Image 1 (cartoon, rainbow, N blue to C red):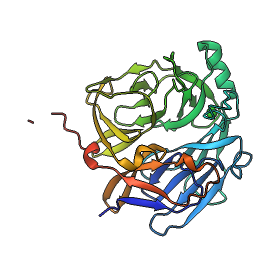
Image 2: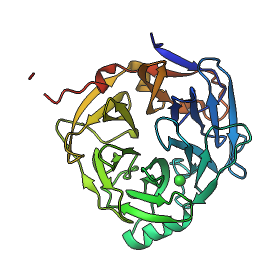
Image 3: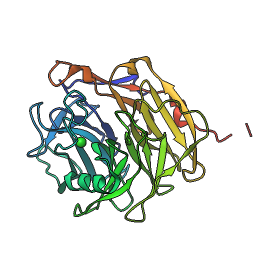
Amino acid sequence: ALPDQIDVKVKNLTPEDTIYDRTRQVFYQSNLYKGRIEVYNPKTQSHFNVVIDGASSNGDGEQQMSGLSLLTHDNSKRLFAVMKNAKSFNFADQSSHGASSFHSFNLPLSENSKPVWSVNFEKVQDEFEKKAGKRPFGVVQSAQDRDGNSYVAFALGMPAIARVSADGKTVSTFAWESGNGGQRPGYSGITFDPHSNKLIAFGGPRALTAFDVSKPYAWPEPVKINGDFGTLSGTEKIVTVPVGNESVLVGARAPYAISFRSWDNWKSANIKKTKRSELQNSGFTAVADYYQGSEQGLYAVSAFFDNGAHGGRSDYPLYKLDNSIQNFHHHHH
Ligand SMILES: [Cl-]
């Protein structure tokens, strides 16, 4: 059976994001403060890191590792790394003009891996502000379409999504909308659904917002929730879980993992929830999948932000979530 927890024993990791590579049997995990990717083998417990020249640090760098994503679920050829500015979410010393960046890597990763390409968001931030009136900042997650284009969510300032071409040459303003106030008015997550061929952003102005990927820009498409999502406060990252021939999206809103399933290509979605008490105050930001052979489960990713950069924590548990959230019934029958 799958374990109730996977205890990652890496000191001062702060895994703001974590994703599993089923093919390679490793997790790719943020190291927030050091601005690097940590690669953890849960079977052997071995780990190593991938540093990014000019961005990684000893814990006090300007840029920090947030989101990680795979090109495809299986046999992924590439991994994408979002780096936010260290001051974006420092609400006592906040900036909307810091350096931030995005990197494409070939898989498999090794200690000496370097990006295929890298971009930064300064110019696109200026363009968003010029056209919409507010400067977005706080890059938190990206999603890749079938052709390898990336769509990067901004959580702060205003709701905004930057597109980065598959070849890294063009960073563009893809989508945006007005915010409705608050410290975190933008999208807290984004994921891609290969079945509908849509992006779905989590949080901000509403629970879920869909976008088509076929054109240079996209209008936000509000998703009607067939149920009661609840508060928008505290939403984090959202992921796509393949369940048979379908997609179930799973978002974090501590202490809940909240899942979604659509039968109409994201015009609407049904909703399920689960929670665990450990996730009340663990820095729960994301859900990861995990496999041992053909056995699959979902695990909560907890950053433990209360540690800071050097607080000494050396246990980063990933906690198993109830499978109820990945079992939808459209309807008795
Ligand atoms: Cl940022």
